[PDB]
Amino acid sequence: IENSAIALSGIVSVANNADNRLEVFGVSTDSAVWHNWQTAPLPNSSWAGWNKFNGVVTSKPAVHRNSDGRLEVFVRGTDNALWHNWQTAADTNTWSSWQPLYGGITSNPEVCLNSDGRLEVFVRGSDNALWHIWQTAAHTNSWSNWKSLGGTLTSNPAAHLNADGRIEVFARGADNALWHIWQTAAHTDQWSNWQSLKSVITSDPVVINNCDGRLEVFARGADSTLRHISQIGSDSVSWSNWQCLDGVITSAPAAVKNISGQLEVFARGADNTLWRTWQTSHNGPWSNWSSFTGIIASAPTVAKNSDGRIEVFVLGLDKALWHLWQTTSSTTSSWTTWALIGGITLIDASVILE
Amino acid sequence: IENSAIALSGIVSVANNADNRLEVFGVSTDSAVWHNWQTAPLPNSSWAGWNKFNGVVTSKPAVHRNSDGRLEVFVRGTDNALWHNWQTAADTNTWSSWQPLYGGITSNPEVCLNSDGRLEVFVRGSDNALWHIWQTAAHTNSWSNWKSLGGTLTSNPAAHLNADGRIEVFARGADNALWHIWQTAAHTDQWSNWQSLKSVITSDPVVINNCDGRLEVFARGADSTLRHISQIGSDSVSWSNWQCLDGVITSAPAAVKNISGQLEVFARGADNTLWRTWQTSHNGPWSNWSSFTGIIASAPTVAKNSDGRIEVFVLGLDKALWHLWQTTSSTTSSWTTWALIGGITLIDASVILE
Amino acid sequence: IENSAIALSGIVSVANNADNRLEVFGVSTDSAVWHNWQTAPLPNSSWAGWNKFNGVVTSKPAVHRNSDGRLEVFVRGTDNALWHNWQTAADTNTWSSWQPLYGGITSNPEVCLNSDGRLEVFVRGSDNALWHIWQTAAHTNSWSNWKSLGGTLTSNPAAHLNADGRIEVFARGADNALWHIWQTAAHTDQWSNWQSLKSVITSDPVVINNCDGRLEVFARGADSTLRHISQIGSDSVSWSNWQCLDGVITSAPAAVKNISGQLEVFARGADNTLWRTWQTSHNGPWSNWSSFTGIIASAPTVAKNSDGRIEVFVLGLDKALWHLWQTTSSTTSSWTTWALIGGITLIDASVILE
Amino acid sequence: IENSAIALSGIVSVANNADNRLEVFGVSTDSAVWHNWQTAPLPNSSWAGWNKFNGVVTSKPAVHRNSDGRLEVFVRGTDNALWHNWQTAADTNTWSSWQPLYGGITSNPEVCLNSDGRLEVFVRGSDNALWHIWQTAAHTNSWSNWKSLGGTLTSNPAAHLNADGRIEVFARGADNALWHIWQTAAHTDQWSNWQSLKSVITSDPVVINNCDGRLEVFARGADSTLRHISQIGSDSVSWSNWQCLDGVITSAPAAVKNISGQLEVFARGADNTLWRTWQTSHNGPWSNWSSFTGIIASAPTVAKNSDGRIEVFVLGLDKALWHLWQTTSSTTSSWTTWALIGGITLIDASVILE
Ligand SMILES: C[C@@H]1O[C@@H](O)[C@@H](O)[C@H](O)[C@@H]1O
Ligand SMILES: C[C@@H]1O[C@@H](O)[C@@H](O)[C@H](O)[C@@H]1O
Ligand SMILES: C[C@@H]1O[C@@H](O)[C@@H](O)[C@H](O)[C@@H]1O
Ligand SMILES: C[C@@H]1O[C@@H](O)[C@@H](O)[C@H](O)[C@@H]1O
Ligand SMILES: C[C@@H]1O[C@H](O)[C@@H](O)[C@H](O)[C@@H]1O
Ligand SMILES: C[C@@H]1O[C@H](O)[C@@H](O)[C@H](O)[C@@H]1O
Ligand SMILES: C[C@@H]1O[C@H](O)[C@@H](O)[C@H](O)[C@@H]1O
Ligand SMILES: C[C@@H]1O[C@H](O)[C@@H](O)[C@H](O)[C@@H]1O
Ligand SMILES: C[C@@H]1O[C@H](O)[C@@H](O)[C@H](O)[C@@H]1O
Ligand SMILES: C[C@@H]1O[C@H](O)[C@@H](O)[C@H](O)[C@@H]1O
Ligand SMILES: C[C@@H]1O[C@H](O)[C@@H](O)[C@H](O)[C@@H]1O
Ligand SMILES: C[C@@H]1O[C@H](O)[C@@H](O)[C@H](O)[C@@H]1O
Ligand SMILES: C[C@@H]1O[C@H](O)[C@@H](O)[C@H](O)[C@@H]1O
Ligand SMILES: C[C@@H]1O[C@H](O)[C@@H](O)[C@H](O)[C@@H]1O
Ligand SMILES: C[C@@H]1O[C@H](O)[C@@H](O)[C@H](O)[C@@H]1O
Ligand SMILES: C[C@@H]1O[C@H](O)[C@@H](O)[C@H](O)[C@@H]1O
C-alpha cells in the first residue's frame, strides 16, 4: 500500500438511543440515507426494518445522541454543504427533514458532544483546513457560524472528549503523519495549535478513552499493520511512543472498551475476514488476532448493547448489512455467526479525499 | 455508637443537568423542597438563587436525570406516599407539580436509572420490606404497580448499576449487617434472593463502580471507622473481605471516582470537619485522611462538574448550604474554602427509621 | 486482648540453603537448638531427621543465608549474650560450634543481609534500646562492636531491605505503636531517627517487599484482627493509612509473595486453625480468609521451595513440628494436609519481653 | 538489513559479585580475557584496573555467579571446545586456570543458574543443534556429559528462569524466527519440544522476568526496530502478540527491571548513540526513546549496582570500555556522561555464526 492510502471504512454509523437500543445509518443504491433499529434493548431483539430518509446525500452519514436523548444525523448534500436531521422526541420514529447547515464540505462529517451538552461537527473544508460548527445551546437547533481551525487534512477527522471535558481532534496531515489539535479549556472556543504525533498512517485515526482517563489512538500504519499510541497522563501533555502489532489489516480499525475496562480492536484482516484483538490485562499486552468466519467487504462498525454485549456490523458480499454479537455480557462470552439485516443493499458513500 | 445507629446523612441531593450544570435539592424550614443551580457549567459560575417547589414533604428528596435529560425528584408526602415532579424540558426551569405515585413509604426514596432508560425507585415499605416501582417506558410518565422485594430493612436502600446493566440494591438488615439483592438479567423484573455481606454497619451503604466494572461499597462500621468491600469480578459472584480504614468518622461517607479512574471518599471526621481519603494508585492503598478547615453539620454530598472538578456540599453551623471545589481538573488540584449558597436555611428531613 | 499483648510466635526459623533446600531450626525440651532439612529440593523430598547443636539457648534462634550460601544461626545464650554458628561450606552438614558475639540481649535476635553481602543483627538491649552488630566484610567472621540505635522497644525487631538497598527496622514502641528507623544510605552506618507509624499493634511486625519496590507491614491490631500499611513510593517518604481486615487472629501473621507477584498472609485464626488470605489482584482487595483443617499451637512459619511452592510449618497439639504445602507451583494449586516431621518435640523459647 | 543479520553485540559480560560489586569481562587485542571490577559497592567506587587471564580464547566470555557467590566464566578455546575458570573464594581475586569442558562449540556460550543452585551452559554445537552441560551438584566442579536438545540455531541462545524455576531457552531458528524450548519440571532433565514464536528477528533474543512472573522477550526485527512479546501467564502456555516500537536500532537491545518494577530497554540507535526507553506505568506503554550524548561502537551491557542504580558499559571509538550510570537510586535519577575504564582496548570476539 502507498503511504497516502486510506483504508476501507465502515459501511454504517451506529448509535445508542436514549433507551440504549442500537440504530444504524447507511446509504443505499438510491444515494439516500436509510436506517434500522432494534425494537427493544434485548439480546433477542428483532429489528424494525429499513426506513428511508428522503434526500440524495454525498457522504457517509454521521450520527450522535444529543444530551436530551434525541439522535441527530449529519451528512454532505448534493450541494456539497452540510445537512442534518433529528428525532423530534427521544426513542421515537418522528424525524425532521434534512435541514441546512451550509458550508463547503470536502470530507465525511465527524460529530462530538461537548461536556456541556452541545453537539459540535468537524469537517475538512474547501481549503483543506479543519472547520467546525456547533450548537450554541445544548440540544437546541441554534448553531454557530462556521469557523476555521487551520491545518491541511488528508484524512477524515476523528474527535473525542478528554476525561477533563476538552474535545481533541485527530487527522492525517499533508505529510501523511497523524496530527492533533484540542480545546485548551473544556467546551470553550479556545484551541491549541496543530501538533504532530509523527509516524505515517494509512487509515483514518480511531480514538478511545481508557479507564484512567488517557486517550489512546489506533490507526493502520505504512506497513499495513495496526499501530497505537496513548497519552502519558498525570497532567503531562506527552504521548507514548508508537507501537505496532503484528498482523496485516485491510480496513480501518474499530476500537471499543469492554465492561471489564479493557480495550479491544476489530479490523478486517489479511484474509478479508473479521479479526479481533484484546488487551490481556490492565494496559497489558495484546492478544494474537482471532478470526471470525466469513469474508467481509467493509471495515467493522462496533457498538455495545444496553447490557454491555459487543455487536459488530459489516458489509457482506451480497452488499447487505450483516452483524454478529456476544451472546452474554461476560468478557469470555461466545459469539454468534454473521446474520443478515436484510431489505436493502448499501454503498460506500464516503467522500473520496484525493 | 450503637450497632443500630445510622450516621448523619447529607443535607441535599445533587444532580447534573443535561448540560452538566449542578443542581441541588433540600428541604427548608417550611418543610418544602427548594432547589438552586449553577447558571453555567463553568468554574466561576454564579448560582441562580433558591427557588421553592410548593408542597409540604416528609423525607429527604431524591433526584435523578432521566434518559432524555430531564431531572425528576422523588419525595415522601404528608400522606406518607411517594410523590414526584420533573422538568418538562431538559435544562429548563419549567417543572410539574408534585404528582402521586401512592404507596406507603417508611424510608427516604432511592432512585436509579435502568440500562434501558427507565427510572426505578426503591423504598422501605409499611411492612419494612424493600418495595420498588418503575417507569414502564423510558423517560415517560407511565409507572408500574408497587411490587415487593421482601427482606427487613433498617437503613435506607442504595441502588447502583453493575457494569452489565443489572441494578443491585444494598441495605442494612435486621441483624445490622449489610445485605444486597440484584436483577439477574439487565433491566428485567427478575431478581435474586437477599444475601448477606455480613459485618455491622452504622450508616447507609454507599456504592460506586470501579473502572474495571467491579462494584465497591463503603459504610461506617461498628467501631465508627470507614469500611469497604468490593466485587471480585471475572464473572465471579464473590466479594472481597471487608477492610476498615483508620480514622473515626461522624457522618455517612460519600464516594466519587475521579477523572483519573481512582476512588476518593469524603466524610465528616472525628473533629467535625470534612475529611478526604483517596486511593494512591490503581486499586491501591488509601491515603491518610486529609482535613478541610471548617466545622460542618451534615455529611458531605459530592458531585463532579462538566470538566471533572470535584465539588462538595454541606450544612453549615448557620444552617445554610456551603460548598467548596477543586479549582482545576487535575487530580492534584488545589481546593477552595467553604463558600455560602445563601438565601434559605435547611433542615434534615430524612425519615427517622426507628 | 490487652494493647501490650504479643501474639503467639512461630515455633521454628526457616531458611533456603544455597541449593534452595528448606532447613528449619527450633528448640527442643533440652533447651538446645535442633535442625532438620529437605534432602533434595523436590516436591517429594524426604527430610534428613532432627540433628542437635550442642549448647543450651535462651531465645528463639534466627537463621539467615550468607552471601556465599552458608547458613548462619543466631541465638541468645545462657549468659544472655548473643551466640552464632554457621555452615563451614554451603549445602554441607559441617557446622561451627556456637561462637560468642557478646552483648546483653533482651529480645529474640533478628538478622538481615545488607545489599553489600554483610549480615547484620538487631536486638533489644539491656536498656531496652535497639542495638545492632554486623559483619565488617561480606560473609566473613569479622564483626563490628555493638552500637546503639536508641528507642524503647516492646516487641522483637523486624528488619527488611528496601528496594534501594537500605535496611529498615520495625518494632513496637513504649506507646504500643509501630515505630521504624532506617539506613539513609544503602549498607552504610548512617541511620534516621525513630518515627512512628501510629496505631496499636499486638504482635511483632512482619514486613515484606512488593514487586513495585514498596515495603508493606502486617501486624495484629488492638481489636485482634490483621492490619497492614505500605510505603507510598515514588521517592516519597510517606506511608498509606492503616487498613484492617475482618477476622480475629490468634497468632503473629506470616506474609509471603507468591510467584505471581501477589501477597498472601497466613495466621492462626479465631478457631485455632490455620487461616490464609491473598490479594485477589495487583495491589488488590484481599480475599476472605480460608481455613486449613487442624488445630495448631503456634503461628505459622512460611517459606517457598525452589519451584515457588509455598510451604507452612507449625507446632502441633503433640508438640511436634507439622507442615503442609502446595502440590504444584500454580497460584491455584491444591494443598496437602498437615504431615508430621517427627523425632523431637519443640518448646517456644522466645524471650519473654515484659 | 537482511532477515539473517545478527545485530552488533555487547563488548563485555558483567556480573555482580557476592558482595554485589560489578565485575566486567572482555577480550583484548591479545585474544585473552581480561577483567576489571569495582573495589567497593559504592556510587563513587574506583575500579581495580585491568587484569589478564592467561589463555587465548575464541568467543565472547560468559560469566555467572554460582549459588555460593563465586564467579565463573565460560569461553570457547583455541580448540573450539568449552573452557571455564572460577573464583576459588567469593569476592576474592584468586582464580582457577582455564579448565576443559570439551565439546565442539559453534556459538558464544550462554550460562544460567538452575533453581537448585546448579549452573547450566547452552551452546550451538557442531551440528548446529542446541547442546547443554550442567553442574551435577550445586556450585561444584562436577559436570555432566554433553547432551543435545536438537533444533537448528542461527543465533546465540538466551536462557532464563521462569518464576516457577524452569529454565527456558530462546534462539533464532533456520527460518529466522524466534524459537524456544523449556524444562517442563523445574531444574530437571525433562524438556519440551521446540516451538516457534514466529516473526523474524535480526539480533540475539534478550529475555527478562516481569514482577508478575511472566517472561518478556526483546529482539530487533526485520525492519530494524525493537520488538517484544510476553507470556500471557495464569498457568497459560500462551504468549502475547508481537509489538514493535518505533525507532531504528543498530545493536542488540539490553533489558533491565528497575527497582520500581518497571522494564527499561537500552540499545544503540540509528544515530549510533545510546538510546533508552522505559515502561511509563505498570505493564504500560513505552516512552519515546531518549538519547545519551556520545557515539558508541557496541551494543550496551546493562547492570544494576548494590543500591539499584543502573549502569551501562559500551565500546568507545577509541576501542576502550566506557560506562555511565544513574547518580541516585530514584527512577528519575540523573545520569552521568560516559567515563573511560582505561588500560586496555577490546575486540569483539563473538563467534561468527554464518
Ligand atoms: C495538519 C497539519 O497542519 C500543518 O502543520 C501542516 O504543515 C502539516 O503538514 C499538517 O497538515
Ligand atoms: C434483608 C434481610 O432479609 C432477611 O434475610 C432477614 O432475615 C435479614 O435479617 C435481613 O433483614
Ligand atoms: C521506639 C520509640 O522511641 C522513642 O521515640 C519513644 O518515645 C517511643 O515511645 C518509642 O518507644
Ligand atoms: C530451532 C527450530 O528447530 C526445528 O524445528 C526447525 O525446523 C526450525 O526451523 C528451527 O530451526
Ligand atoms: C441531503 C439534502 O437532501 C435534499 O433533498 C437536497 O435538496 C439537498 O441538496 C441535500 O442533498
Ligand atoms: C466548511 C467551510 O464552509 C465555508 O463556507 C467555506 O468558506 C470554508 O472554506 C469551509 O469550506
Ligand atoms: C458475512 C457473510 O458471510 C458469507 O460468507 C457471505 O456469503 C455473505 O455475503 C456475507 O458476507
Ligand atoms: C408533596 C405533596 O405536596 C402536596 O401539596 C400534598 O398535598 C401532598 O400530600 C404531598 O405532601
Ligand atoms: C410501598 C408499598 O405501598 C403499598 O401500598 C403497601 O401495601 C406496601 O406494604 C408498601 O408499603
Ligand atoms: C462551613 C462554614 O465554616 C464556618 O466555620 C462556620 O462558621 C460556618 O457556619 C460554616 O459551617
Ligand atoms: C549457646 C551457647 O552454648 C554454650 O554451651 C554455652 O556455654 C553458652 O553460654 C551459650 O549458651
Ligand atoms: C546488646 C548491647 O550489649 C552491650 O554490652 C550493652 O552495654 C548494651 O546495653 C546492649 O545490651
Ligand atoms: C496439625 C495436626 O492436626 C491434628 O489434628 C492434631 O492432632 C495434631 O497434633 C497436629 O496439631
Ligand atoms: C582458553 C584455553 O586457554 C589455553 O591456554 C588453551 O591451551 C586452550 O586451548 C584454551 O584456548
Ligand atoms: C557441543 C557438543 O560437543 C560434542 O562433542 C559434539 O559431538 C556435539 O555435536 C556438540 O558439538
Ligand atoms: C563514549 C565516548 O564518546 C566520545 O565521543 C568518543 O570520542 C569516545 O571514543 C567514546 O566513544
Image: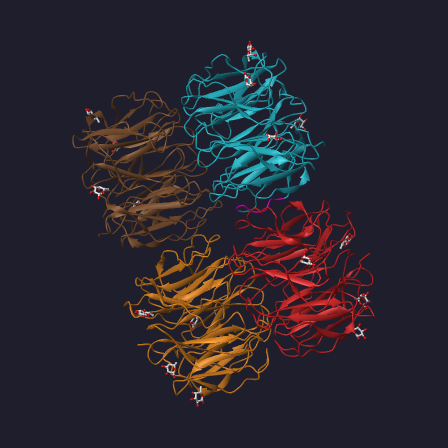
Chain colours: A brown, B cyan, C red, D orange
Closer to the camera in the image, D294 or A270: A270
Task: Report if residue A143 lies within the magenta region.
Answer: no
Q: Is residue D52 left or right of residue B348?
A: left
Q: Which residues are magenta?
A: B282-287
Name the spot of residue C69 as percent of width and height, x first: 61, 73
Q: Looking at the image, in which quadrant does ligand 8 appear? A: top right
Residue at point 39%, 58% (across, down): D239
At a point 66% along the width and 28% down the height, the residue shown is: B6
Q: How many marks?
A: 0
Question: Position of B317 compared to A211: left or right?
Answer: right
Q: Is residue A165 visible?
A: yes
Please identify the quarter of the rendering in which residue C70 is found.
Answer: bottom right
- Quadrant holding the N terminus of chain B: top right
Quadrant of res A54: top left
- The vertical placement of C233 against A102, above or below, is below
In the picture, the quarter occupied by the C terminus of chain B is top right
Looking at the image, is D248 positioned above or below residue A191? below
Front in this rendered view, residue C340 or D252: C340
Where residue D242 appears, as percent x and y from the top left, is: 36, 57
**Residue name at image x 45 percent, y 15 percent:** B94
Q: Report x, y in % for residue D220.
A: 35, 64
Residue closest to the far left: A30
- Assign the magenta stretch its main secondary structure: loop
Answer yes or no: is residue C167 visible.
no
Of residue A78 and residue A262, the one placed in the foreground of this image is A262
In the rendering, at what x and y percent does residue D221 appear?
33, 63
Question: In the picture shown, does residue B320 fall above or below C133?
Answer: above
Q: Is residue B284 magenta?
A: yes
